[PDB]
Amino acid sequence: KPKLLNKFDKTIKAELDAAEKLRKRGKIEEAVNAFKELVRKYPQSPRARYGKAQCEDDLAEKRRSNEVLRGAIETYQEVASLPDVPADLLKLSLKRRSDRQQFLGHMRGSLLTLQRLVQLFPNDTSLKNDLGVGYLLIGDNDNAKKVYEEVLSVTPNDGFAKVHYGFILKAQNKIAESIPYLKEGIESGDPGTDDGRFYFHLGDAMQRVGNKEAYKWYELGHKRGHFASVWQRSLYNVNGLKAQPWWTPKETGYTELVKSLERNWKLIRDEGLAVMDKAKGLFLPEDENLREKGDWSQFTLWQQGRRNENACKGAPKTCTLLEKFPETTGCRRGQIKYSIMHPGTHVWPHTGPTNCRLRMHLGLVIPKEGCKIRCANETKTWEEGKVLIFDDSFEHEVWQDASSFRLIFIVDVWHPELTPQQRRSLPAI
Amino acid sequence: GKCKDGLGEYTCTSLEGF
Ligand SMILES: O=C(O)CCC(=O)C(=O)O
Ligand SMILES: [Cl-]
Ligand SMILES: [Fe+3]
């Protein structure tokens, strides 16, 4: 189907096919030497150059080598700099270049490549959609929003653009405005719209506005394989882990950690209160748009399994205590943090990102009435000096209607059924 | 930004190649 051979390349098609046959047969080393010979003999051939890049790409996969892949990324760009490159080949080469740049985490480099593709092919709407993803990956929602507005101005029923536009609106707390874009985009069935993120945020947007249809989308997302259950909607999962909203210490196996937290809870409390009194700026407001109303801040000692040294200057005894427990300090998909919540606070129903952690709450200052936490269908309360444990990959919700502040200590642990091999290799969250 | 308590980011992990 695609036209990849320019005038000269058609005259050397037999040599180009022989080299490509070696690549398809998995003889990568012979293939790179065949294409390097073609690039030597025909230095202007775009197909030979693209063959060299594809072989380096395959070699990077075989060796799991970032350095080899960086070579491929340069050769893909070289294809585009050659004379008389067929449009189909030019697009394929730069699209793979951007894709591999993103794989390596070169998000700035990928963005430049995507911008060049849109400049070269101004009528290709899918390339503009790819550029919007480039901005989303780097955290530039404003430019991403502009891109999808450009896409929807010419192709209003592009479902890929709709779900991404709706995602951005929702992330900007434009909850009502995001629902039709997310809903119409998923319903469009366009490639790229059957994605767990869009089911996740549509249902949540509906919940925030009181739309009872929300759980019909959770059930569908579960039916389509995006969620373990309609209750447990985390998207960064290891399949097969024991799934239940509430856990006892004995069930987790981390009874030594729990005993230490409960025996020593007052020192943890006292350091948290001292920061509240003398270093209040270390408590940072929650910034994930999870509050309907109220005040909620956190003072984080560990995140992604990394100790915050300056924070531990503010709670040195607590940090010294916790350092004995790698099941939490090494949990690279969790945090260790103080969490203060004040009256008038309602945290929206929401889900954490991963089923790979369990979340412990140690009560430090708990008002007698007005504070409670729901996980799945069960609501509980904290007690000073006592640990609660829940799987925050299940939907959970918090209320603070007391007449004074509520302070807890949050300690994430690896899910106990994750092997040591999984705990060292899982990407941090 | 990072997904700490929620799942609000487009991606919650950072790509580092192989
Ligand atoms: O109650 C708090 O302080 C935080 C509740 C919550 O959403 C969580 O711990 O994941
Ligand atoms: Cl215990
Ligand atoms: Fe939460």
Image (tube, rainbow, N blue to C red):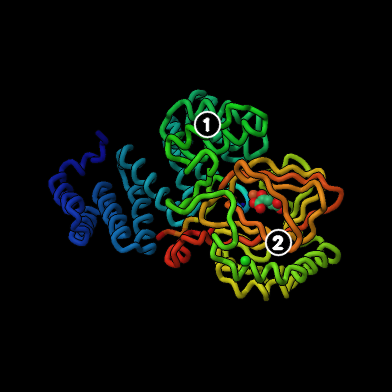
Quick check: A323 above or below A368? below
Q: Identify the mark nearer the N-term, 2 or 1.
A: 1
Label 2: state its secondary structure.
loop
Name the residue rendered at 23%, 40% in the picture. Answer: A5
Judged left or right of residue A147, residue A224 is left
Identify the subunit bearing mark 2.
A
Name the residue rendered at 46%, 54% in the picture. Answer: A241
For the residue pair A327 and A301, the one nearer the viewer reads as A327
Q: Residue A283: x and y, percent?
A: 76, 59
Judged left or right of residue A54, residue A166 is right
Choose top left, top right, bottom left or bottom right for residue A266: bottom right
Q: Which residue is mark 1?
A: A217
Q: Label 2 amino acid?
A: Lys
Residue A135 appears in view: no
Q: Label 1 amino acid?
A: Trp
Q: Residue A171: x and y, percent?
A: 63, 40
Q: Quadrant of the N terminus of chain A?
A: top left
Q: Quadrant of the C terminus of chain A?
A: bottom right
> Disc 2 and disc 1: Cα gap in Å?
37 Å
Q: Residue A386: which numbered mark, if any?
A: 2
Name the residue rendered at 28%, 49% in the picture. Answer: A50
Identify the subunit bearing mark 1.
A
